[PDB]
Length: 398
Image: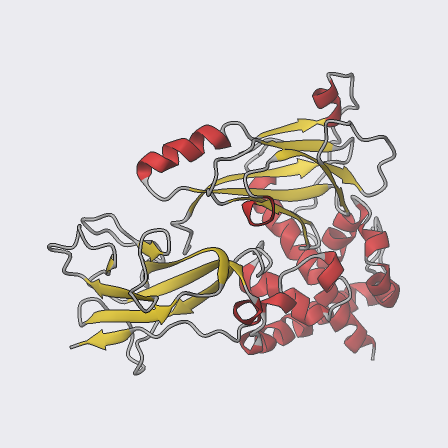
């Protein structure tokens, strides 16, 4: 009844609460300046990270035209865990530009100089930039480009006197309730309006933008809601297979079910919408045995995945979830480093024995311990995005 409402209220607030906690534990307690650039991680790209704050005024992210063929992406998400911008080579090619992020309610004209304007519903937005680098010397090229990326407030951009940056007083996650954290974030922007359909339902629970006064009953419902809410999320998690329902924009997920949207944060917070990047993980061989380089040699043979940009498969150790040391310092293979057989099949051979393989582009080193492989798809088609496409099997070699 009210317990049911409280559960749904918490599930709606979950994505916002976890985004806040993440922001607090990173930017707040490490005192990261805003509007400035600061396992199982990519062996595919270099990165730039930061947090934009458009409360006082808009902010412009500058991206230089890039060199032909190099993958790059500027990805931003709001505090409700919605991707609100994904500018990249996939859809722009080499064309960079001046990208302005403004609060949804910001009144004002746009400089002729600005390429695109992104209206954001939270004043704080997480920014992540990725620039492809396929080898150490090529990385030096990409680095010369990343150095040109810039973040400037509109006033700074125009060389004008601007408003003083907003100074916030942040609720401590260790001693506050989820109601105060969520209401705090909701207040800092236009989220109240963008989430009206949800907020109209959970008002009696105490979820409301800027609300700090609560009744005993609301505090009680909040505790019960978080408990049942989390239980529900844990139980629902393993049943999720379609990434398109978990990671997206307000246009595609704004009205989607909250528990499913919430799994986006639960399973892979800050993840890119599948159309930009999808992934697959394999921990076992084709017969159900754990992948382990100390016990076998493996082989993977498959047709090229349907991607518009590129793909890759990377090796990680199960123990530290990090790439594993090997003499070739080779941790991944992909279409940029291999060529398909006369019949267009790619064949990856894996072993801990890397003697005489430096001249083998299809050879992928694997550690003398349990390992897993992560396949990444950039510009994947629907089948890959939805979870339908299955990762090629890795078989033990005699």
